[PDB]
Length: 235
Ligand SMILES: O=C(O)c1ccc(-c2c3cc(F)c(=O)cc-3oc3cc(O)c(F)cc23)c(C(=O)O)c1
Image (cartoon, rainbow, N blue to C red; front, side, top):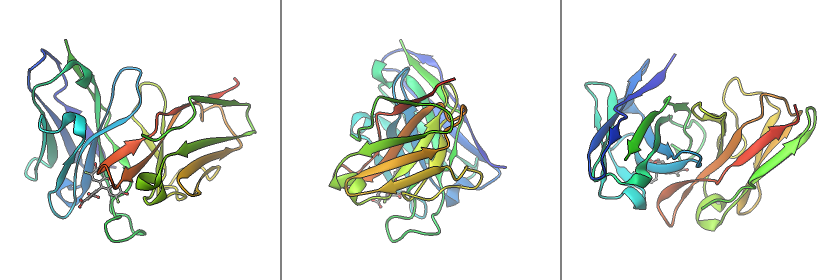
């Protein structure tokens, strides 16, 4: 199997620089797209920066634009994130993910979902709406609703992630309604206008987690995550 190993995380002063790293093993990183998503302590997911597969086109998030840089190193089978002029809000665990080539899908929409995440690395410095929380009992049925706008969800492929406290996020649904190998079919995704929906029939005790949705936003030119839903199963 494949994995991303991250290192570089450290306690630093404000204004300091710091270089994070996301190394690939089991596969060759140069032939693949990737992203950097961070998660402040007690916050939700937030896109930061990314790399296009066949070229080397970077895109950055408005917050960290001009401070952060993202190069690759085909020789060390990895990709670095150069963070400069750090600020206290940058405080968070930074994840890195590969976006595989989507067999389905189409021109300009071939790298939509993040299917292999890293384990994360802490950097300490001295939008789409979902409900805050839903609840149910085992055997029942929840529906997590993700609503946005034309710019993003109406036009673009949407994807859902799952996340137990402390662990890295996991890909549940991509391209609106598909699911990767080894995901129970009791997970179902759909879309209707400018809002998508995650569906869990036959709820179980392990399903208890945080659920995010995500989609590219054409007008902002960023990748967007939802605020997140805390699913609670009555246990
Ligand atoms: O301007 C471009 O060529 C471009 C623009 C945006 C993306 C991009 C997309 C595009 C989509 F259509 C999606 O459904 C999802 C995305 O997700 C992305 C995530 C990354 O952060 C990144 F740097 C770029 C993209 C992208 C890519 O590498 O796939 C390339």
